[PDB]
Length: 349
Image 1: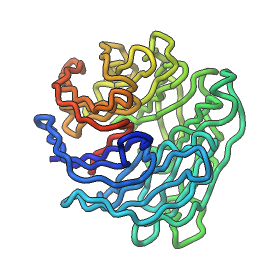
Image 2: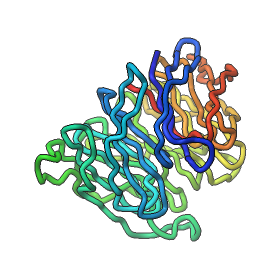
Image 3: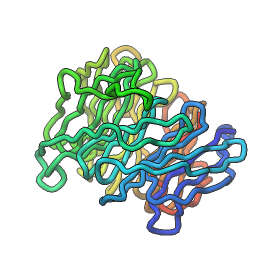
């Protein structure tokens, strides 16, 4: 079976991280262990699955990135250390094996943490702060970094800024590590790529073919499709994922076969919008819509592409939907995984 890690908001019953075994052939999950850490909103396992890095989303000086040693054979967690981010509300985290990068929502910045030899985190190495505002007076008063993604080629990093309707561009130094002083992230050219005012860039994902990227906009509720090549994003299409103006869109994922794209919506008509991906031009065509549990801030598709699990924060459950290989449509198999406020799901490679 696969090993599954679940992040939560810990104000209620949840204590932090939760590990499970997940059978991707019949959708059954078996609980393993847990790790007490506050607000592990987003997390990412190391390529070898020996470590797990999770944020501690706080709107104060407690905001941090946590380093965990992970024994998947036992399914247990071992906290190594915690380092402060440069800014408030870190809500997305990634690792290139040498450094961990955090996107700070309230700080309007991104923080880089070099990884020590033992897998723990050295203190924040680089903290890039952004400035600006947007169309929406309430939600775009200043920058709000919601996502960081290293391109398929590994030479660049894009940081979605919901507060200024931009996707900031950086050049990635593959040789930057804790051993040297090589700058890991450097401002690229151009400094960013702009999207329609009021969009509210949230999450960005890349297609398996590595030639296209898709963005889900939290405020506008649209999905913008981009052609991608050597650090360049060119807009090819915009389409609505949310059609009721809920201004609460969330996550975005493409099925392993690259034939379908899913985008989640919250606040009104909670669910996922389902699109077919053109095999030649990568453009999207809406084919269905699935109402889910309440507040689907995050979801994931199993490696074999058979199941799609949706973390429903307000319904306190992770719903399991079987995917129809040919239509992309979903079917609830009734195997809810109960957990208080789940907001992130990952599998251990």
